[PDB]
Image: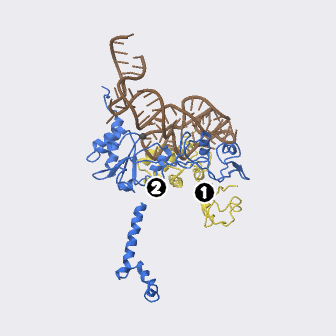
RNA sequence: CUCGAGCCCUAGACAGCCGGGAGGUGAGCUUAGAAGCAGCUACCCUCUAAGAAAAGCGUAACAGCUUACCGGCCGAGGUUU
């Protein structure tokens, strides 16, 4: 048996409860309660004191599904549109995965998010492609800066 | 003659950018780049930044730039050969040669190499999928037994340590297991501080011996604290335990 | 063997050898799975000295081997016509 399970819920049954009994029980319930529900995670064995965990962070392409609605991507990107995703919603997806991205701030992290958004025909406002210019011109600074 | 006609643009722009970087960061130096994978080098540059900045270019273009400056920075040129890169910081030189060690070189160990570290595979549950993986570990190290959820690792013992190279197949099962048991690092060849250049070999020695002389100094005060016939704060227990203690040495002893 | 022309080169060319070819990401669509590489569309973005939404092998599909691209060693011509 192993330790892992999706869901943003609290203690989703058999992977967690049965295996964890001595002497730790249910004391790990706080960590997997993350808003998005799904957050597959892995719990490392620990001492008797508390517990030890890490958080596996969901992919970016699937992270914009739980925001923009219908999960089917564009057959032809920059042609057919899903369509839209709000600008401040992109701010949220960007703060989500810090280590999964190489950026030193949200500004650039957003660019990667919208970078992928070109592939799915996400058309943030008029078009995903115009995004770099716009944000480099300081358009959305009110959000990030 | 073998010089070109017109110096290409980008070579001029890069010398400018290098000079620009050099101009900031009042402490500047050249280090290594050693050999180091991209993802690992990123993660060295990705540590907080904000302290030092790593600047890489051609050794000739770094050497151009040090010649445009050089009120102090000329002698930094004799320390440039090999793979090498510029470092600069607002921090101290002595604190500069440190923090470079912080989160450095996990080093996955590609096949055909000898690592000074321990290549020992641990015990636990990986369980990629039931299959040849059970036999993959058999041709290298302690057997993998499949218990009830997936394949697992039995023995925590060593496979290979030092004094010889790595198997090719091991290198692939060390890659699947996600095992990176080697330490190389980003060296430091020299650094420039204010008026003078610091060579790591001399004057750059380091921390226990400092923490050894620093506790020895605090123990130097508490040794003279109660002999002062004075009152102290944390040394207040000096007389408290000497109250009923040393009084008998003048009474019960002789 | 001889006579031209263009381009590149000591701010280090051409070749070789060594090192690095990174992250979003296994891009989206298609598909049971389509992971650079069956197919359709797009081909953005970060970290960078540099690294394609992959030029060619390769896999049932991932491995895996290279090419682009960058750095080092070397040092004087190289390359097209
Ligand atoms: Cl070197």
Residue sitting nearer the eye, A110 or A25? A25
Q: Quadrant of the N terminus of chain B?
A: top left
Who's the residue at 36% across and 54% down the image?
B204
Q: Which chain is brown in the rendering? A: C
Check disc 1 and report the residue beneath it: A36
Which colour scheme appears in the figure? by chain
Q: Which chain is yellow in the rendering? A: A
- Residue B16: x and y in percent read 32, 42
- Horizontal placement of A11 versus B201: left or right? right
- Parent chain of label 1: A
- Residue B108: x and y in percent read 54, 45
Who's the residue at 66% across and 56% down the image?
A3
Q: Secondary structure at mark 2?
A: helix
Who's the residue at 50% across and 52% down the image?
A87
**Callout 1 crowding tier (Cα within 10 Å): few <14, some 14–19, many ≥20:** few
First in sequence, mark 1 or 2: give its number. Answer: 1
Q: Residue furthest front?
A: B254
- Residue B151: x and y in percent read 70, 49
Q: Quadrant of the C terminus of chain B?
A: bottom left
Write down which quadrant ligand 1 falls in.
top left
Check disc 2 and report the residue beneath it: A143
Who's the residue at 72% across and 52% down the image?
B149
Q: Which chain is blue in the rendering? A: B
Q: Secondary structure at mark 1?
A: loop
Q: Is residue A107 visible?
A: yes
Q: Residue furthest bottom?
A: B251
- Parent chain of label 2: A
Asked if marks 1 and 2 touch (Cβ < 8 Å), the reply is no
């Amino acid at each position: 048996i192993e330790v892992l399970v999706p869901g943003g819920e609290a203690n989703p049954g058999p992977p967690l409860g049965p295996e964890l009994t001595p002497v730790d029980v249910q004391a790990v319930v706080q960590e997997i309660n993350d808003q998005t529900a799904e957050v597959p995670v892995t719990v490392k064995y620990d001492d008797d004191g508390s517990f030890e965990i890490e958080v596996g962070v969901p992919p970016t392409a699937e992270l914009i599904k739980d925001e923009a609605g219908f999960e089917t991507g564009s057959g032809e990107p920059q042609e057919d549109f899903v369509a839209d995703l709000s600008v401040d919603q992109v701010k949220q997806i960007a703060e989500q995965k810090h280590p999964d991205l190489l950026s030193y701030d949200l500004t650039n992290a957003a660019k990667e998010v919208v970078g992928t958004c070109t592939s799915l025909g996400v058309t943030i406002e008029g078009n995903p492609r115009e995004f770099k210019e716009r944000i480099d011109a300081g358009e959305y600074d009110d959000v990030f800066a | 003659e073998r010089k070109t006609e017109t110096i290409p643009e980008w070579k001029q722009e890069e010398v400018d950018a290098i000079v620009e970087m050099i101009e900031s960061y009042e402490s500047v130096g050249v280090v290594n780049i050693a050999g180091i994978p991209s993802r690992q080098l990123q993660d060295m540059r990705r540590d907080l930044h904000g302290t030092a900045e790593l600047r890489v270019s051609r050794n000739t273009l770094l050497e151009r730039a040090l010649d445009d400056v050089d009120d102090g920075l000329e002698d930094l040129n004799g320390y440039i050969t090999g793979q090498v890169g510029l470092i600069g910081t607002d921090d101290n030189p002595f604190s500069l040669f440190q923090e470079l060690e912080a989160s450095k070189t996990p080093a996955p160990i590609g096949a055909g190499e000898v690592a000074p570290n321990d290549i020992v595979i641990p015990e636990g549950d990986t369980g990629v999928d039931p299959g040849p993986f059970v036999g993959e570990l058999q041709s290298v190290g302690a057997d993998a037994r499949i218990q009830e959820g997936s394949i697992q690792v039995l023995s925590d013992s060593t496979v290979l340590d030092t004094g010889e190279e790595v198997s090719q197949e091991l290198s692939n099962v060390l890659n699947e297991l996600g095992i990176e048991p080697k330490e190389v690092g980003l060296d430091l060849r020299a650094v420039f501080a204010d008026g003078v250049l610091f060579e790591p070999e001399e004057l750059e020695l380091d921390x226990x011996x400092x923490x050894x002389x620093x506790x020895x100094x605090x123990x130097x005060x508490x040794x003279x604290x109660x002999x002062x016939x004075x009152x102290x704060x944390x040394x207040x227990x000096x007389x408290x335990x000497x109250x009923x203690x040393x009084x008998x040495x003048x009474x019960x002893x002789x």
